Length: 167
Ligand SMILES: Cc1nn(C)cc1[C@H]1CC[C@@H](CO)N1c1ncnc2[nH]ccc12
Image 1 (cartoon, protein in one colour):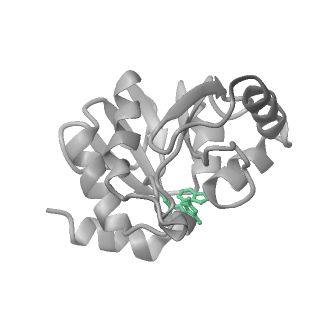
Image 2: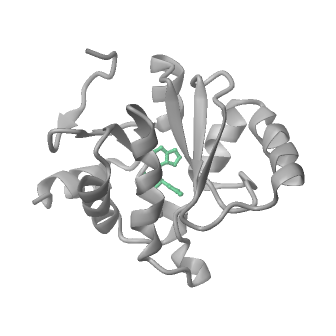
């Protein structure tokens, strides 16, 4: 039993809700919140911009030190950093950004990072400003993640379509 509330159950391990991931994290304080990161950990917009703003830019400060030490992530890769006031940890995961021409096949690799964590709050990778088809992202999520994932979808219209079209 966990404290996630109001989710629709899609499969044995995948759950979905129309929610603002910032507000969900603040309420639940999950062990792991997933960020829709880029390889530079520049949290300027999209989910990343919103999560960072909610930390009063502390996420960005920590991220800049991470990059200065380690260099950029790989597309499809991840790193674990602090969750600040939102979660114990933040798993920064880089899905391909179609608006950069990045291989959508890397979306499965991106979701594989979730399997290193027993329970996560997460957005649909490569959705929103990363330009991928959110229906496809949900399919890859369900077919790749085996741990318990609670998916937050900001846009109410898109959520209804993901549910209604889910196979
Ligand atoms: C814009 C945007 N850019 N990216 C990378 C994702 C999004 C939006 C669109 C689709 C949805 C994916 O779950 N997503 C969010 N979902 C939940 N909380 C959120 N807070 C802020 C954004 C957001």
